[PDB]
Every structure is written in C-alpha cells, then in structure tokens.
Length: 50
Length: 67
Image (cartoon, rainbow over all chains, first blue to last red):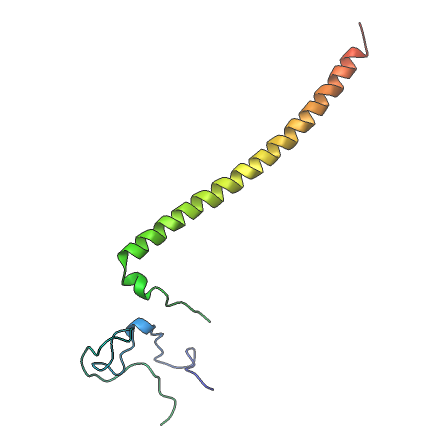
C-alpha cells in the first residue's frame, strides 16, 4: 500500500483521530452513537488518486 | 513512527486524568523511594560487615603486642 509522505508533501498535517471530520453530520463523535454534527467537506482521507 | 491517540476519552473524562496523575505520583514515590532504600540498605549492610571484620582484626592486633 501507499500512505502520505509527510516529509516530501508540502502541506502535510498530522491530524489525530479527534479532529477528522468525514461523514460529518451523519455519524456520532468517536462512538457508535446516533448521528450528530453538520455536513461539511472532509479532512481525513488524504487523497492518493486523481 | 509515532503512535498514541488513547487520550481521547481521557480528555472526555477529567476524573480519569486526575486518577492517572495520582497513579503517576504514587508510582514515582514507590519506585524512587523503594529503589533508593534498597540500594542504601545493601550498601549499609556491606559496609557494616566490612567494618565488623576490620574491628575484629584491629582487636587481634591490639591484643598481640602487650606493651
């Protein structure tokens, strides 16, 4: 597999689990609870295609 | 490499953080004090044994020259 190359990427940002918003407004915060939050573009999966 | 995110519900729980701090303080006290006391007791025992042996030798030497 391949992952983000933190050294060579210009705008790398080591983002912990606490601050990754994907599927926001549709999944509970860090726990299999009910949905919460608002829709928003996302931050975490760093794209490796396109 | 770096690996730790376990602080999530630690941030979500102030009491857990306080208990962890108390545990750290108790671990510090136990480890440091017990290690220091054990090393000191070992050193004191060795020195006392050597001192007793030397005292015996000095007593013998004193007895073996009756001025």
